[PDB]
Amino acid sequence: MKTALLLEKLEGQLATLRQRCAPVSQFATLSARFDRHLFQTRATTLQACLDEAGDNLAALRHAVEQQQLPQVAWLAEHLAAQLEAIAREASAWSLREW
Image 1 (cartoon, rainbow, N blue to C red):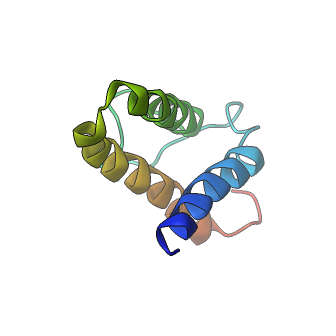
Image 2: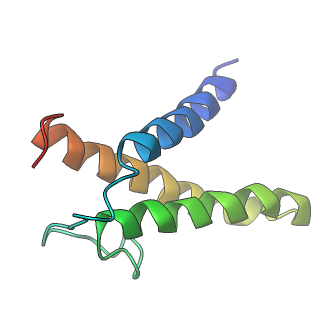
């Protein structure tokens, strides 16, 4: 228990957010307060953030087969921070378009 909840939330939120924020590549725009630590180098726009996150979680999922647990720590921090950063911005603007 517990450990299973964080998994459903991470994957659940990532799916929901990606769905609601799916059609954002058209007006994807990242603020000037972007952080290289929380966001990747490619993270230049909204669509870029979601895309980068998708590639991270994907590799992290398959990495389990290569016993890349030690790497899960870093990938986890980045992935977790990414979803948090996106949810934070969307939360501020509130569900009411830009």
